[PDB]
Image 1 (cartoon, rainbow, N blue to C red):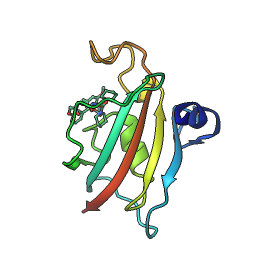
Image 2 (cartoon, rainbow, N blue to C red):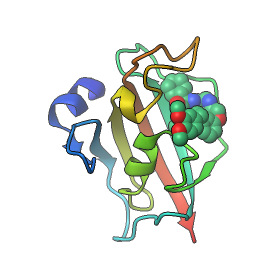
Image 3 (tube, protein in one colour):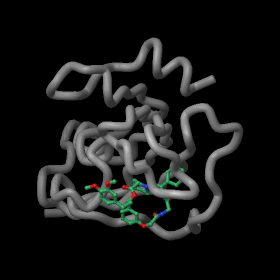
Length: 127
Ligand SMILES: COc1ccc(CC[C@H]2OC(=O)[C@@H]3CCCCN3C(=O)[C@@H](C3CCCCC3)NC(=O)CNC(=O)COc3cccc2c3)cc1OC
C-alpha cells in the first residue's frame, strides 16, 4: 500500500539526506508558492503507525488543524514536509522516528521507535 510505496519510491525531503522523511504527492496542488517559516498553515490530515491497518480516527476531520510552520509546534517531519506543499496539495508522508517521537514515543498510542505515516491536505496558509 501507500506506506510501502512511499518507503521504496518516495522522495527524500530531508536536509541530511537520510531518507528520514519521504514524500509522494497524492493530489497535485495549485500555483508554485509554498508556506514559509512562521506562516500559519491550515491542513486536514490522517495518520497512523506505518504498519498500521487503519488510519487513526481520534480527531474531527471537519476542523482545520492549524500551526505555525517551522516553529517546532509539530513533529519535525511535518515542519519539513508541509513546507514542500502547494495550496490544495494532498501528499503522503512517511517519517522515521528521529523525525517523529523518537525513543520516548508518546505512550500508549505511539510506541518507542515508531515510524509514522500521514496523508496531509494543505488547505491554506498566511503570513
Ligand atoms: C517539536 O516536536 C513536537 C512537537 C509537538 C508534539 C506533540 C504532538 C503533536 O502531534 C504531531 O506533531 C503530529 C503531526 C500533527 C498532527 C498530529 N500528530 C500526530 O502525531 C497524531 C498521531 C495520532 C496517532 C497516529 C500517528 C499520528 N496525533 C493526533 O492526531 C492526535 N493528537 C493531537 O493532534 C494533539 O494535538 C496536537 C497539536 C499540535 C501538535 C501535536 C499534537 C510532539 C513533538 O515531538 C515529539
